[PDB]
Length: 170
Length: 170
Image (tube, rainbow over all chains, first blue to last red; front, top):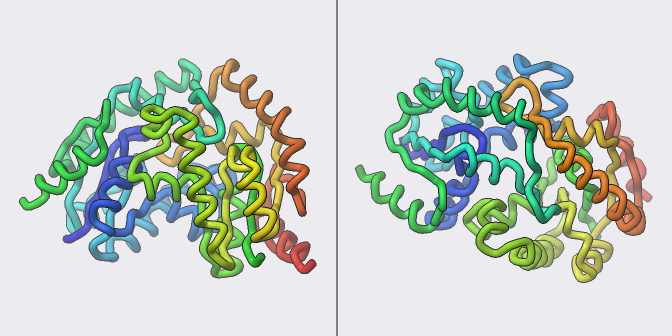
């Protein structure tokens, strides 16, 4: 155990809540996406282009295997990680599982906001529908693995993260 | 000196090329955005919401100051970092400056591709125009600071990163 796993779709607040927890605890925060890019030595866009989604899922499972071995870490889990039974196995076995929820509107804010640009980017309605369809069919699975569940709309990082830390223990 | 600074707009390949360089050199790759979120203990979306762009630029400059002190690192620099004279000062003084270029089409690929989703997200034409306007007015500034310049379309990470390492020295 000892690991904290944060799960949910893109824009669920994994990075946000994940950053606050790592502050309050001096633990190292990992992001499975960034870890994959690091080991690959290329960005996610290169992976999908040269190897397709399948190529990414492969690399994703290798990294999850490796990360789950580490102890006392915190992990912002790529939304697609729980699609694989093996990943769900290692995760449920090696740490607590927190499912973070957010409205479609909260999602689009986080996803769209870039540092170099004042207003967030907006996605096409086509893409938005795709996202809401994902929300639809991945939610139940997330709920399954969820030891604990929290909304992250109107988020007060510090408040929620300490609250989360209390709900851990037990 | 000793630092490698990667600059450009979102989707310029900073993370990609940055990951390949860190592999080939066993150096630590930093991303000013992630560093900011880490110290803040919240995501960029929270910063812009509770403090606006101004609040972000403040935090951005503190982190750039701190990172520039570090030695022999690699840094994927947030697109907005070079807007501040002080940042441009510390950067040009403490390392090499690589400007990475990419077509609008290459940009939209990298920006839109999420790990958990097969096809990339597409942004609205409104947002795309905003991006091309940024490209327009930030390019010259990037070119100014650029010690070295590379395109990243049809990127062969390994090939370009070694090529970059050769062009360093001198």
